[PDB]
Amino acid sequence: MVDAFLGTWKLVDSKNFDDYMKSLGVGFATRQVASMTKPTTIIEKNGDILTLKTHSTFKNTEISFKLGVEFDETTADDRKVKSIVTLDGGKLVHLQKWDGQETTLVRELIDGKLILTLTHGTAVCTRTYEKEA
Ligand SMILES: CC(C)Cc1ccc([C@@H](C)C(=O)O)cc1
Image 1 (cartoon, helix red, strand yellow):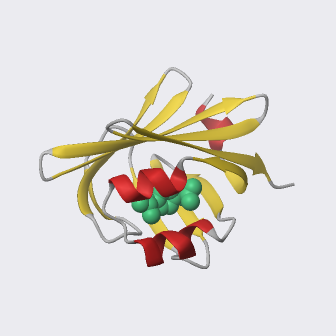
Image 2: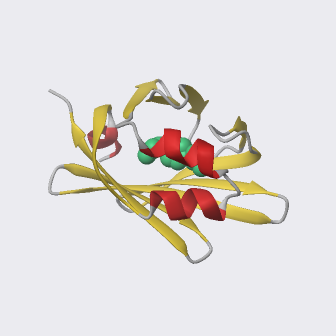
């Protein structure tokens, strides 16, 4: 159930993140900073409002949203996007759209770990998170 996403998650593995960021036009200097920290993601809920916080040395971000209701978002890399978060079976799907393109940030729980798959065209990144106690 949706509740299994709630809590505090720490990055423990990454594949293809530099490649995903390059695919979004993030410059090398910014990619180096973004890749050299293990971020923390906090997923919270109050009524039908979900909040996702990312804490890192690169940027702190916070978004709030209702499932299935489009919202304006300014991403960590300063893209102004049109976003929506949905639940597709066990997948919490964050879609970002801008300028005729899109990216998805998909979260799934596998063996108690939070797997974040970031897709932008042929660039696919896997970020693996573990729950903090
Ligand atoms: C283009 C990038 C900078 C957008 C971005 C993707 C993933 C994260 C968090 C979840 C992360 O896993 O580091 C933060 C920002």
